[PDB]
Image 1: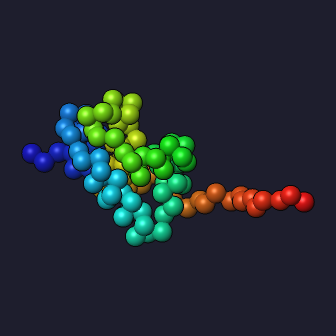
Image 2 (image 1 turned 90 degrees about the horizontal axis):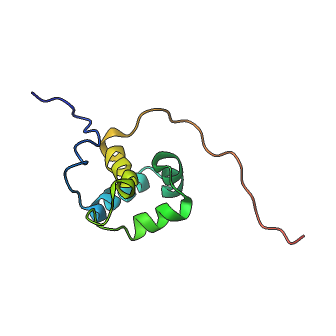
Length: 101
């Protein structure tokens, strides 16, 4: 009977989603936890820091996204429920400030 539950991307290979409400749900769940959507994009989604910014700010509809364009949105959809519980516990140790002298 009920057999999957975490809802792997194979559901979304066929069916459509509201990419605007998806990015919304994601942005909220991240904000509710003080997660920088940048580092989420970098690690979880796997995307460049500006590419994911443009994504979450001004997505395209599912109908525009090809399979390679849906990949980050799929990982977004999963992460909502799935949380992708590999591993947590490491910030990016590093920083810089400007200098001129």
